[PDB]
Image: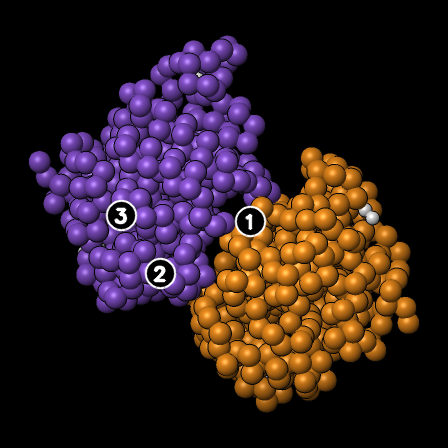
Chain colours: A orange, B purple
């Protein structure tokens, strides 16, 4: 296999030979991309979700560590408003611990950056990367727009302070338009952060039926539909000629979950981290791209897709090999 | 604990004493109801979903068995159009095996009827009940309206053949209106079947933003919003003053998943089987209620709920004890 990770062959989204019953080459060409780069711990990706299980054996090596925090001293050493935020934060309780007690955030994290070639579990689009978590969704799914905003502000704070964080994964949605959320996203744009967002799983047209945050018109929002192992648009996926940008694998995605385990989930929530992961991989090759250049590169470098054509801006399905190639520098 | 099932105390939806961090008595009063009835295997509930793991140690005793089929003989002995449909069918492939290879259908099945007092795992609203599966969603989430209709038709076929199938659990949604699906549901009403449906997890109003199948106006459709351990409406729940009927526990629900395991999920998909389970438990006490009487009883016997008031027709949260009392013949 492309790596020595024992579950590699189940990862059709990264490499598809038809082994899960789909169509050969309906994938993002990850092994090809890995000949150029397998990623850098110096690239930081924020996951805004139910948290990140940074203790999972297949994520631990890629957990972000706050260089400005002394662990466990009960002091907010870097003065960012959260005490002892070594790996990220909990936006509900303000505790400096993004530990995932639900599962969803760990799953998306593994797709972005499960440790590669370590002989255990799976592997992310990046073999090496730094993942910082902000938990705004509780173990029972409880959360708020205010919480999501606290997360975005926190991540923007890290970036403004010099943390190399230019990609946010947002595998969540709900509610209507919020000016406060739009404004938080606008601030992230000024900080050069790409805001990747899931299109939703209700199989409707988002141009007629807006879904947030993917429908925010902010230029740095990159809205992702889900595709399957046959390169169809996933039957559950929402779409939108103007409001959704491109697609990526989200049907039957195996990844890390808490308690040192692995599980298969389906949703636009799973497509999103392939794209966030690809963005991080691109930034390991060309850090000089503006956010908009990065976004457009991910869109334009994808494979033309019959199902996504006319149902998304780019009509393409993610191809991280071509993204790296097109990224030069 | 109310039963000897080792995970019972995690099931706040059945019995809440604040042990999961919520509010004492924000629950459906299951232990109270069980003093009246713990269910009957003669009540049959259909689950239309990713399938049912009928081999799960905490579901096997309550898996429906088609009395009209000789297992494994390659013959459709009961002449219902499906070969060897012992526990139900796969509507994608037409094979008579609804085995869950995804997990979702098994999770909702456990909430309806995980075996009670068997010293294993969890317990459903019913300790004893018969659960038949129709799998229209694949391992990777692939499905279609055609598949859902095939499942409804299959269940209606069982009922019309003399099976005591009175309740359908539909913890799924997506797509636009389908007249053919509406017609399939009408056939189910004609057959005296209650069609329980999840309201959706996008925190929007279904009255202005229709969600299917929740928004079908069929009288036998019972549309369910999610509540949490504090008796709030779950932050993710969709609502609808006229298009959603009542609420039930859906935040942080522990139940059965395939591979002899247990997992905690959140969503209206988890609230739905509390109601489907309660419907079946009511029918063990008063089998003579009509579908519409049953629907109205579940809504009217619920506890008044401040959050759901003004956001659903009944403004109540499920109470199965009160349902059993109100149903007394
Ligand atoms: Ca390939
Ligand atoms: Ca290729
Ligand atoms: Ca700090
Ligand atoms: Ca500190
Ligand atoms: Ca109680
Ligand atoms: Ca009570
Ligand atoms: Ca048959
Ligand atoms: Ca047979």
Residue drawn at 35 percent across, 57 percent down: B226
Q: Is residue B117 above or below residue A122?
A: above
Instruction: Report the chain holding disc 2.
Output: B
How many angstroms separate mark 2 from mark 3 (CA)? 41 Å
Left or right: B246 with respect to A264?
left
Q: Any atom of ligand 1 within 8 Å of the CB at mark 1?
A: no
Which residue, given by chain and number where applicable, does mark 2 sit on? B207
- Label 3 belongs to which residue? B1
- The quarter of the picture where the C terminus of chain A appears is bottom right
Determine the chain carrying the residue at label 3: B
- Mark 3: which secondary structure? loop
Q: Residue at x 50, y 36 (%)?
A: B146
Tell me residue A323's x, y (percent): 82, 62
Q: How busy is the neighbourhood of tag 1: few (under 14 within 10 Å), some, or many (20 plus)? A: many
Q: Nearer the viewer, residue B211 or B88?
A: B211
Q: Residue furthest left?
A: B329
Label 1: which residue? A236
């Amino acid at each position: 296999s492309a790596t020595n990770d024992p579950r590699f062959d189940d990862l059709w989204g990264l490499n598809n030979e038809g082994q899960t019953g789909g169509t050969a080459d309906a994938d993002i060409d990850a092994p090809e991309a890995w000949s150029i780069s397998t990623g850098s711990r110096d690239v930081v990706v924020g996951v805004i979700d139910t948290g990140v299980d940074y203790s999972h054996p297949d994520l631990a090596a890629n957990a972000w560590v706050n260089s400005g925090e002394i662990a466990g001293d009960g002091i907010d050493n870097d003065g960012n408003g959260y005490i002892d935020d070594v790996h990220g934060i909990n936006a509900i309780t303000d505790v400096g611990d993004p530990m995932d007690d639900e599962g969803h955030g760990t799953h998306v994290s593994g797709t972005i950056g499960a440790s590669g070639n370590n002989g255990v579990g799976v592997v992310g689009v990046n073999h090496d990367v730094s993942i910082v978590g902000c938990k705004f969704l509780a173990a029972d799914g409880t959360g708020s727009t205010s919480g999501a905003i606290k997360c975005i502000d926190y991540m923007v704070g890290l970036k403004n302070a010099g943390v190399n964080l230019r990609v946010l994964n947002n595998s969540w949605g709900g509610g209507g338009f919020s000016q406060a959320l739009a404004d938080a996203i606008t601030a992230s744009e000024q900080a050069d952060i790409l805001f990747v967002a899931a299109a939703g799983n209700d199989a409707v047209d988002n141009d007629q039926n807006p879904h947030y945050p993917s429908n925010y018109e902010n230029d740095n929002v990159l809205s992702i539909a889900s595709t399957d192992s046959r390169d169809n648009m996933s039957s559950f996926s929402q779409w939108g000629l103007t409001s959704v940008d491109m697609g990526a694998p989200g049907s039957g995605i195996l990844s890390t979950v808490p308690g040192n385990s692995y599980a298969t989930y389906s949703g636009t929530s799973m497509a999103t981290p392939h794209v966030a992961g690809a963005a991080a991989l691109v930034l390991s090759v060309n850090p000089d791209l503006t956010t908009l250049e990065l976004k457009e590169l991910l869109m334009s470098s994808g494979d033309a897709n019959a199902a996504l054509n006319g149902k998304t801006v780019a009509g393409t399905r993610l191809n991280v090999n071509q993204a790296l190639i097109d990224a030069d520098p």
